Length: 185
Image 1 (tube, rainbow, N blue to C red):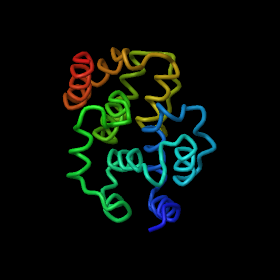
Image 2 (cartoon, helix red, strand yellow):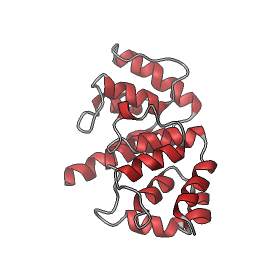
Image 3 (cartoon, rainbow, N blue to C red):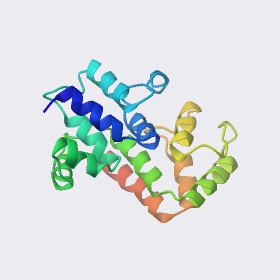
Image 4 (tube, one colour):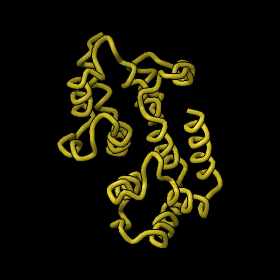
């Protein structure tokens, strides 16, 4: 089967939410300020090709992205890859190419409900005045804004924890599990 055609086929099944998620998960290869021209998934895939992160004989990053955005359907149809295989692969030390920090933030975004997102905005406003926040922003946009204002980063989780602890233990658990494993180092 044809590599380029397959990339297009996958791209056609990815929606605007998927694209925004994939862009977020690609941050420690495609800097935030270089993502604006990327208007669809195929364009993201072409940027990854240019970086030799994606090629005919190297599908590992594409598989990891699709797995972490939960497009198990596309992994089966277009990449003949199962959830079981990805769990085994990504649980092997060194195999994952997305940073534990970036995965951690993404996993918080997956858990947060619409009402919890309203709470996150309100609580962050109590903790910080530097961020520009509005009602239309999703949690990933909030994280990007927190990073812009240098109140969130790999070793700077204080505000994130203060907000999450007031929303749901589940979120704080994601952060604490990440922190523990990171210091294990």
